[PDB]
Length: 261
Ligand SMILES: Cc1ccc(NC(=O)c2ccc(CN3CCN(C)CC3)cc2)cc1Nc1nccc(-c2cccnc2)n1
Image (tube, rainbow, N blue to C red; front, top):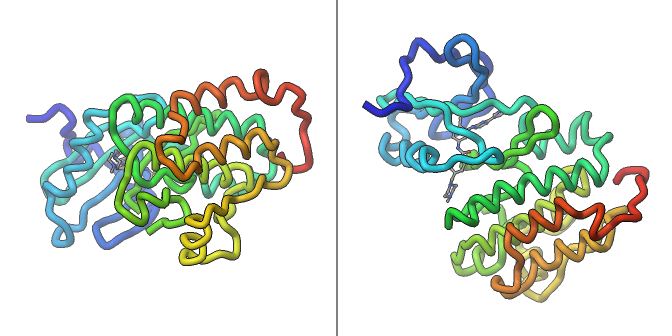
């Protein structure tokens, strides 16, 4: 049978990390040596084949900025096993104890890594549909990987996708722009004070988030390209990656540290 299959005895579940109507998530050990994240399926909540769809996808994806599948147990009770990311979610990391020490340089490097991951998704002709800080994992050495915890996130979703169900890599680019604001505000909810309804009215009317405090205008400019009304006007993740990797030399060479960024 499949080469991803592992014996049940090789997986230890050590710390519960969350729950849902379809299962749970745990940190644990695989082969008594490898720390892992584990996703379970509640028997009786959702069909196995519908659940293992995710694992099937994850077998065909391989990239250093994508959370990596490690193994599965594909007879109920089901287990999906991936690499473990020591710092947890980008969102939690941004707003917690570490967040006070991150400046533009680390934050833009995180963005470039995320764009790199998304650029692979771009080349592979996949769509993400839920790119946001909550679906980014952080590891040692500020390593950031794209994940999908299957967690409507209107505030992160391109208008044409939210309104008309048109989800492309270009609506992923819009989400990335919103992700840029999470990075520069240390994980704050976008469109502060506005509910979903006003967000949709306002954005359709052409409103866009302002340059966050201490964020270089040139980075907010980039956010605004990600938020172009016309999907095809938005940049590629290939471009986004290259722009963020070169940012402090090509775009903002006179950058000087500040109080928060
Ligand atoms: C245990 C597991 C099982 C499945 C997944 N799957 C994904 O992360 C994922 C990523 C991309 C795709 C591709 N897909 C293309 C099509 N569109 C519509 C959706 C995305 C699918 C699944 C992750 C995990 N990992 C996981 N889950 C929850 C929490 C954590 C975690 C928490 C703290 C520290 N380290 C890890 N780790």
